[PDB]
Image: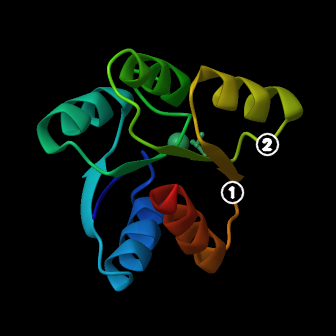
Amino acid sequence: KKILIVDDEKPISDIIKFNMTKEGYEVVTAFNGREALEQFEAEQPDIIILDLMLPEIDGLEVAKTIRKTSSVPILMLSAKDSEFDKVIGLELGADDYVTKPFSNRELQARVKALLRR
Ligand code: BEF
Ligand SMILES: [Mn+2]
């Protein structure tokens, strides 16, 4: 399975990439919302892990535009942790929303759960 991870902070991207690689997934990375849409279109990932505070196009906008054409599972992963943030993330089309700082094991279990369903 192929995972697109979208995050502008390279240290975070690297941590998540390391963890997905350990699970046997193929990893693609994007570092802003424009790269996220371009990678989504070129790579057709099986799942997207999506940060929200991103250069160029923010993650909510990325999720909304992906949803215009695709039902690819989207797991938002953000320091934005308010009721409002989670609710609008899910309403716009995210299948799950996990906050930073996060457990690596839980992230792995949530990716598996989304892929399962
Ligand atoms: F920059 Be992410 F929304 F933590
Ligand atoms: Mn960010």
- Number of residues whose C-alpha sits closer than 10 Å to that of mark 2, classed few (under 14), some (14–19) or many (20 or more): few
Between the residue at mark 2 and the residue at mark 1, the CA separation in whole angstroms equals 8 Å
Left or right side of 109 for 10 = left
Which quarter of the frame holds ligand 1?
top right
Residue drawn at x 46%, y 43% is 73
Q: Is mark 1 within 8 Å of ligand 1?
A: yes
Q: Is residue 66 left or right of residue 34?
A: right
Residue lying at 69% horizontally and 47% vertically, measured from the top left: 79
Q: Which residue is mark 1?
A: 100
Q: Can I make out residue 56 in this image? A: no
Q: Tell me the quarter of the picture where residue 91 sits.
A: top right
Q: Amino acid at mark 1?
A: Lys
**Residue at x-position 26% and y-position 63%:** 27
- Residue 57 position, x and y percent, is 41, 21
Q: Say which mark, if any, is on residue 15.
A: none
- Within 8 Å: ligand 1 and the Cβ of disc 2? no
Image point (45%, 52%), residue name? 9
Closer to the camera in the image, 106 or 18: 106
Q: Position of residue 56 (x, y in %)?
A: 37, 22
The residue at the far right in this view is: 83
Residue type highlighted by circle 2: Asp
Residue at mark 2? 81
The part of the image, by quadrant, that contains residue 10 is: bottom left
Q: Tell me if I can see residue 117 in this picture.
A: yes
Q: Residue furthest bottom?
A: 22
Q: With respect to residue 95, does 23 lie above or below?
A: below
Callout 1: 10 Å neighbours few (<14), some, many (20+)?
Answer: few
Measured as percent of width and height from the top left, residue 31 is found at 34, 43
